[PDB]
Amino acid sequence: IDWDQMNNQVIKEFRETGGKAGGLFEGSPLVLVHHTGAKSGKQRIAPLVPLLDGDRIYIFGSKGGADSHPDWYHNLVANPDTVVELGTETFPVKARVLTGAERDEIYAKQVAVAPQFGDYQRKTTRVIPVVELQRV
Amino acid sequence: IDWDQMNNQVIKEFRETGGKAGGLFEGSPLVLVHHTGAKSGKQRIAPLVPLLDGDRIYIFGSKGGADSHPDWYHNLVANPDTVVELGTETFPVKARVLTGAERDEIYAKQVAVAPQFGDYQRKTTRVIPVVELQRV
């Protein structure tokens, strides 16, 4: 499975369907998150599965339960003013890293939607980040 | 995007990761649902995004808001005794088609997780099916 090629194809499908990617992605929550390299300044787009809790948008640095954070997490910490595409809209956001009880409560809500997040946190002692993409 | 080839690749990845497909699928709820052709008796596997509400499992015949139901829906109506793969487990299930208020309540829970389901139901006057996969 070529994930790098399938990234650009997913971005295309998302944009052409108004954020309603089809096929095997049909029912998944999905956002396109732009992120700028902490060192390079190079911009990339990450299709990510968010928690859409009411009108708020959260993303999770699970990386499959790896012992490292995903690059997009470090990029949003360094450059939190970015853009997200959700549905038919694109809007400026400020990334906010959750901590403490708020982070635990949001993580638990995601475990309730997608139980693999329980496994991911069991697999590493790294605290998996929760990032709110706050609409500006 | 070759969905037919990417079906077998997703099935492989699901089985090898214990139901924790990675890459662009990392955070999505996902089950593999076996279904037998209503006329042919031919067996197929559909990777589908369920609602995992407590310990119950529901799937949605949205078909992108099309005016027809997906083939797997007709197949489960004809042959409701089947198998689902969830996480690291595989278990026999009986498919039950929801109706009335119960169907509306479960559909609303899925719209709250994945808002595109609101769009899909707006797009067709066909009532989108909700099917519980009941563990035997």
Image: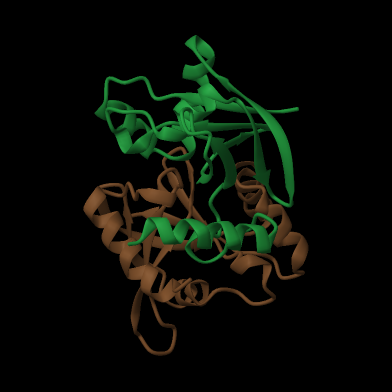
Chain colours: A brown, B green
Q: Image quadrant of residue B126?
A: top left
Image coordinates of residue B62 in percent, x first then y, are 39, 33
Q: Nearer the viewer, residue A90 or A24?
A: A24
Check the picture and name the quadrant holding the N terminus of chain B: bottom left
* Depicted B62 relative to depicted A122: above or below: above
Q: Is residue A12 visible?
A: yes
- How many numbered discs sit on the rendered protein? 0
Residue at horizontal 56%, vertical 47%?
Answer: B29
Task: In the displayed orientation, state which residue is furthest to the left.
Answer: A16
Choose top left, top right, bottom left or bottom right for residue A133. bottom left
- The image shows residue A92 at horizontal and vertical percentages of 30, 60
Q: Is the residue B91 above or below the residue A67 in the image? A: above
Q: Residue at x 34, y 84 (%)?
A: A42
Residue B76 percent across, percent down from the top left? 53, 28
**Picture coordinates of residue B25, whole percent (x, y):** 51, 58
**Is residue A131 at least partly visible in the picture?**
no
Please name whichever residue, A33 or B31, is drawn nearer the observer in this view of the structure. Answer: B31
In the picture, measured across the screen, residue B6 lies left or right of residue B53, that is left
Q: What residue is shown at x 39% (from left), y 33% (from top)?
A: B70
Q: Residue furthest front?
A: B40
Quarter-of-image position of residue B86: top right
In this view, the residue in front, A18 or B20, is: B20
